[PDB]
Image 1 (cartoon, rainbow, N blue to C red):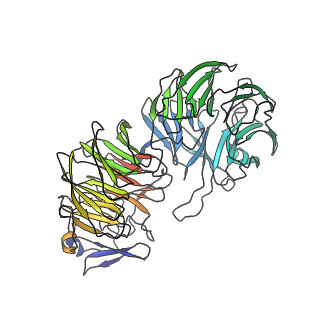
Image 2 (cartoon, rainbow, N blue to C red):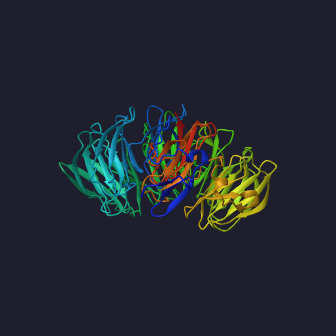
Image 3 (tube, rainbow, N blue to C red):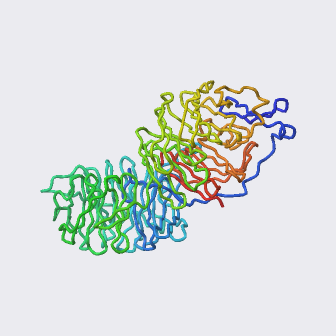
Length: 640
């Protein structure tokens, strides 16, 4: 139930599920501690400033370029409007889980977005829905088919003939229902089982608002909107062998349907027909994931496997060709820029800006797998992320771009900077760890301690020791000299019955705290690799950092009835009296410090899709950095 206070022993006992965890307060606090006392809201707030990463790996048709100079895409639960020239981001966060599709209205301003089904902190199932909003005011305009869609809204599009008064969508109902709406009236015009296999696109005909084309696994149908029914007319390849997948679709100025497929074939279908009139055979070696009709009649072609970006004439004759540096990976989306500008989104979550000629450089990028590793620079406005994708990235937090990106052998899980700022440590899931040169990226040392996951990598405030948390239930201690460049194994702290979740050094570099899977709080003298069991000595210790979720100064960030695994991360600002957490429900919280009373108030901030895995303030408390875990993203909140 509720936590209990002990005057005689000077502690509060909080309850995680059943088991109680005993947290000791300082002696000077015991005299007037009130269990029923409240902790205030923080004096500051957070404001999303930047999202890192682009969801390209497992999504299509989610890259656009508004006439305002804002590149629009999404990732996790946030839609990003990125003005490359101004280096500024704006965000629409109306959704409460992963955005899956996005379409821009013919008006160039009204946007529409879809979403997967949710699961909340309770957690019940939050149905998938569509949102129509204004890109100018970022105000929501309508909320469509709240109870109607199932699983997720994967495809969406405005009709372009009439002025986009209509909208079509496709859920993942396993019957993949296709529906049409008068979005401005929030009314459903009609619907019908579009397919029983994955459908990858749905789009209105440029000149006739009554026709929707959908494509996907062995599927290219032509739907006609008659009153409140959809009439299906399958595509008849005839002389062309039907491709495994029809990946994408668009339309010529003359109203023909144009199709890219698994085979690498650009197929033209005559206006009004359900049959192929022209066929670029083997336009690409691999499959064709992106098609884009430039304003000037040029058709641009994007190859998945072959990484080629081909320019085609109005008459489908090869005009120009480029290859995207293989580092970026296979193309997924293409969008028309201003002038000769072209944008590409890749399977590796890069968004490149180049030209048909063409010099493609990233303007956005991020991790492509589950992310847990976060470390902040002691003196510079930089930070390091490292994930299961084997990348360790050193970010510039003012430029919002990597300083460098090291690719290591094994999936990374944790990291830490040396207080000097000269080197940075990186832990992996194997028990192996590395140190790299902040400046040069050169390796500095490698070591293997245990064979399990290294959850935590932290130097002591004085930089004389490295404390390494392992899932084998031990904490490995190294002595560090020559400014983080020389190491020597001091020994091991053992006594935990479970994997190490969190560590903190004391201000004087003498002590260390521990949290574990058991939910026990242990203390240590790393220099001696021995556990300090005596209360009177550890209770009044003053700690350098507060990344232990289990502790008296920090408890109360925990919600009632909370489960031990509900909060992945906690941290304190360096100077300001703030705490921040990341929970298993995609939420970042801002509390005041200290947070030592039950049911602490907090400001809650959404964006991350699943689990906020880590959280940490920049060195001047200018920003908070969160990691999204499976959602792949890094989010940069500014303190206001």
